[PDB]
Image: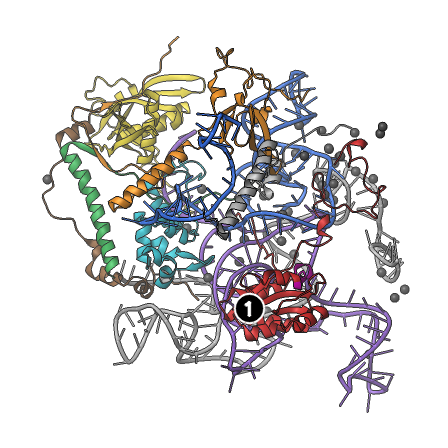
Chain colours: B red, C orange, D brown, E cyan, F yellow, G green, I blue, J purple
Amino acid sequence: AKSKNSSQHNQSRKAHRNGIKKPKTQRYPSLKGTDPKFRRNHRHALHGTAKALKEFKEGKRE
Amino acid sequence: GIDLRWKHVRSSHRKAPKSDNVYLKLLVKLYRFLARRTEAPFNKVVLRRLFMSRINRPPVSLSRIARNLKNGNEKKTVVVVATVTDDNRLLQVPKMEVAALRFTAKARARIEAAGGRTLTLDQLALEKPTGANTLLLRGPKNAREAVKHFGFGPHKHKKPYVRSKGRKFERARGRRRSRGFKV
Amino acid sequence: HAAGLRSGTRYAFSRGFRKHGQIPLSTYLRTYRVGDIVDIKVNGAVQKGMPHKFYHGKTGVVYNVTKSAVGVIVYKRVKHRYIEKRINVRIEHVKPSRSREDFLRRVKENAELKKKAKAEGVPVQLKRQPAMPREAHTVSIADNKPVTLAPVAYETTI
Amino acid sequence: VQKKNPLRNKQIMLRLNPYASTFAKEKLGEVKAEEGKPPKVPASFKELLHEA
Amino acid sequence: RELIYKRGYGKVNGQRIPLTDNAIIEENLGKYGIICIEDLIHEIFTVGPNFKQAANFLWPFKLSNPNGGFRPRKFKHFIEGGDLGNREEHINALIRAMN
Amino acid sequence: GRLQEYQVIGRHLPTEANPNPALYRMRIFAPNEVVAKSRFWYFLRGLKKVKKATGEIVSVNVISEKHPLKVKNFGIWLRYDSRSGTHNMYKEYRETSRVAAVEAMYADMAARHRARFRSIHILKVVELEKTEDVKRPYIKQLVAKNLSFPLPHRVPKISTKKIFSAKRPSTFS
Amino acid sequence: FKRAEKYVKEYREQEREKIRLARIAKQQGSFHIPAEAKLVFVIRIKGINK
RNA sequence: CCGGGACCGAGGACCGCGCUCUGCAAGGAUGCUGGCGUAAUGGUCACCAGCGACCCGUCUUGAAACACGGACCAAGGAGUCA
RNA sequence: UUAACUGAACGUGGGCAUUCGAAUGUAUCGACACUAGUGGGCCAUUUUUGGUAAGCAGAACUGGCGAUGCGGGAUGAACCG
RNA sequence: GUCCCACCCAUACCCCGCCCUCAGGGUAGAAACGAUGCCCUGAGGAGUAGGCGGCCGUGGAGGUCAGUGACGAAGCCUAGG
Ligand SMILES: [Mg+2]
Ligand SMILES: [Mg+2]
Ligand SMILES: [Mg+2]
Ligand SMILES: [Mg+2]
Ligand SMILES: [Mg+2]
Ligand SMILES: [Mg+2]
Ligand SMILES: [Mg+2]
Ligand SMILES: [Mg+2]
Ligand SMILES: [Mg+2]
Ligand SMILES: [Mg+2]
Ligand SMILES: [Mg+2]
Ligand SMILES: [Mg+2]
Ligand SMILES: [Mg+2]
Ligand SMILES: [Mg+2]
Ligand SMILES: [Mg+2]
Ligand SMILES: [Mg+2]
Ligand SMILES: [Mg+2]
Ligand SMILES: [Mg+2]
Ligand SMILES: [Mg+2]
Ligand SMILES: [Mg+2]
Ligand SMILES: [Mg+2]
Ligand SMILES: [Mg+2]
Ligand SMILES: [Mg+2]
Ligand SMILES: [Mg+2]
Ligand SMILES: [Mg+2]
Ligand SMILES: [Mg+2]
Ligand SMILES: [Mg+2]
Ligand SMILES: [Mg+2]
Ligand SMILES: [Mg+2]
Ligand SMILES: [Mg+2]
Ligand SMILES: [Mg+2]
Ligand SMILES: [Mg+2]
Ligand SMILES: [Mg+2]
Ligand SMILES: [Mg+2]
Ligand SMILES: [Mg+2]
Ligand SMILES: [Mg+2]
């Protein structure tokens, strides 16, 4: 027999029952999808920055 | 009518231990009194952790204690509301004063042989009623086989429920491109 | 019925009246940085790098910069949750957004207001207030005699 | 244990506002307007009022 | 004045506490210069700089139905002859009946 | 209802391009000043390009009847909406005040043409100074010379709680 | 006590000042537009259904 | 500022805000008096009276249904174990 | 990456507040685990599509009945309160 | 048809008592407490499918009540509490 085809009648209320969850933002976003050349350079830039920061405490004194 | 979204909402945290241990009940009474009559947040945290289930009190190993004993924490009293276990990988146990819910036999023996000291939580309450000069430690909560299965789904890299491991168990059609698609 | 990619984009993706043909080159001359806030507006004359019709008229944050396109983060409402979508959009469909210009001008105005208030010894008001009810005032009818109006009688105009 | 209306219980009223007794005694609710012969309403005002 | 004096309740630690003493008002609003019920009334009536704090400290007033009733049909606008909307100064009679 | 004539003076909000805007005055018959201001804004929307949001009320005053103890004839020109169109009609009343004339007008329109308050526009209310400018026979017969009449078949006043009477009442007083 | 005394005096003076400003405008032949209301009391009159 | 009426008396040493301060109407009723001391109050049952009140279970969007099962009663009777 | 320290990204060090930069509320924030029933719906305002129309058939938003008693509409799943 | 006054009553609103639920506090140099108790305060209460908690009842087992009973156990009847 025939029946109802489709409906969105109750969906808004069901969605709002426990709130519309918006994923919280973070200080450091994922570098996924970023330009691989930029990622490759950024890796070594971070390496050098950490090395320089450690030498600063150990006697480099920048 | 009053038009409230929430009514009779119960607190989602434990208010007492589900355990029937008589000595745990005595310890809970002691730390209830301490948390009521002292300003120290340490006592309240200890009291709340005394209610917790075993999975909420993962074990802490001697090596985990030794990691946190570094960088100016050598003379602090280690407080673990959990079981303290031994670690074979740690060959030299540093001198330490640890108050824990319980110790394994090997952990207690090695702590005492290294010149350290072992305390119960009531002894800790006696000597440091406000938790002064204490280092409060927790074990790895997520380091558990069951947690590896939680949230299994596409592109989530969790552990499936399988009876065995091998080429014939969940490794074809849905896991490689040579069998239609991968996950 | 159909559910193709560009279904229902007859007017949204079309170029306006007397807006066809050559594309101004300031679009290509603009520069974008990661973290910039951009408005997405699909240009119908550029079929490469076209975002889906959902993202037409949406505002997002640049998360990736490439040779001729930018990656934009948008938040899309599906069922009871928000999903973080990442779209690669060519520059022709991207415009820098004024959605933060008021705040970006207010921050520096507040900085100068703070330094001037500290110099002058009197605090000022940094936060914006909503429109307040009007104060008491006097209106003189000298050379402004009120004009008496009455409702007009009905009559046909056809 | 019992909320007492200060508008009915004078003791509660004096507890909350010690100035209530002085207000009642000095009759600050019956202060009459300052003296002075009132100026009459201007003829322009009256003409505008009855203009139409 | 009458609303604060008769139906005055403060939100103290999430609880609805009757304003039977000036100590409660001083304890919950003393940092804003409000230490008495007359101070609270003055702040509300004059819309002072701490009107937000005073009004939010006041628990929402729970009035009774008006002693003389409403207009014949109360769910039209006041202009149409009902009770909804802005009746301006005429809300004082409604407050006197409802309070 | 029980009405009162209000002089309502309003104004467009002053702007830089138009300081000191024109002041508009209307005479509004309303139960209260809230309704008076509402009707003022309604008619000013009808007549000029001014709204309540883009304007303000300069003044609201009560226009009392200057001789409420003198009997007068009033002519009211009004525009009203029927079920099938809009019409203008002129009617006459015999009252001691403009407010009373307007109340009688509202009751009479409701009684004879089923016209509600929402569908009537009072174009003009004028006190007819003379006698020969009275145009309606139902006012002429009241202003007839040496007018006097009896009150036949008048029912005596009996308390509604006096259910039973021991003698049959008379209707001659 | 002193604060309440000051408040009572302030209320009376504000009322009298409004009255005298309106009167002086009327005398000078102008209209005094009073300040728009700064406080409202709002009462929920309908129920919680529909 | 004066009256007239109704319903109610929660708590149980003091503690507090206070006032018109030897005291008080101020963090919840006391004082005086009368009749009776028993079926008097009160409970239960039967009946009359005023108002109210469709037959349960079930499937169902919708059951009092002109939808199905049920004449009545006792006992048995259906999420167990590995 | 640029002709180049000149940019990009991430930082070190120093400074800001006589005011953390609209309103209102916060009578609840977030994460996790395990699992029930449901997956025939129907009615109403407004917008509607097919149909001459239907107590007909099909959709959008919101509110309802289902799952809900109570006062009113005599009588009623949905109307008013 | 319009306008006005008084009045009638819902399980709604306001004040008070009580029940429960939820929440927030106090309570040991213990004259101390079914601390799983007591004391103080505030708010809330519809519900099919369904979930959870607490309790009542039945056959049998261990411990205990130095338990009840032929001077009457169990069962059964009872406009008696
Ligand atoms: Mg079928
Ligand atoms: Mg279906
Ligand atoms: Mg939930
Ligand atoms: Mg309730
Ligand atoms: Mg993916
Ligand atoms: Mg092959
Ligand atoms: Mg193959
Ligand atoms: Mg109370
Ligand atoms: Mg004079
Ligand atoms: Mg009455
Ligand atoms: Mg009514
Ligand atoms: Mg009896
Ligand atoms: Mg009967
Ligand atoms: Mg009946
Ligand atoms: Mg059927
Ligand atoms: Mg049935
Ligand atoms: Mg039938
Ligand atoms: Mg059937
Ligand atoms: Mg069948
Ligand atoms: Mg049968
Ligand atoms: Mg048997
Ligand atoms: Mg049986
Ligand atoms: Mg499911
Ligand atoms: Mg299906
Ligand atoms: Mg399912
Ligand atoms: Mg169906
Ligand atoms: Mg239909
Ligand atoms: Mg059908
Ligand atoms: Mg059903
Ligand atoms: Mg209902
Ligand atoms: Mg009914
Ligand atoms: Mg029907
Ligand atoms: Mg209650
Ligand atoms: Mg319930
Ligand atoms: Mg058996
Ligand atoms: Mg026997």
Picture residue at 38% right of the left edge, 38% below the top: C107
Position of F7 relative to C12 (above/below): below
- Compare residues C13 and A55 and report the one nearer the observer: A55
- Compare residues F20 and I62 and report the one nearer the observer: F20
Picture residue at 61% right of the left edge, 63% below the top: B49
Picture residue at 48% right of the left edge, 51% below the top: A59
- Compare residues B111 and C39 and report the one nearer the observer: B111
B58 falls in the magenta region = yes
Instruction: Tell me residue D22's x, y (percent).
Output: 22, 62
Residue E84 appears in the picture as rendered = yes
Query: Left or right of C77: which side holds E9?
Result: left
Query: Left or right of E29: which side holds G14?
Result: left
Position of F70 relative to J49 (above/below): above
Which residue is disc 1 drawn over? B75
Position of I72 relative to B92 (above/below): above
- Compare residues J16 and A39 and report the one nearer the observer: A39
Query: Left or right of A23: which side holds J73?
Result: right
Chain letter for the residue marked with disc 1 in the picture: B
* Magenta highlight range: B53-62
Residue G37 appears in the picture as rendered = no
Picture residue at 11% right of the left edge, 38% below the top: D39
Label 1 crowd bin: few (<14), some (14–19), many (20+), radius 10 Å:
some
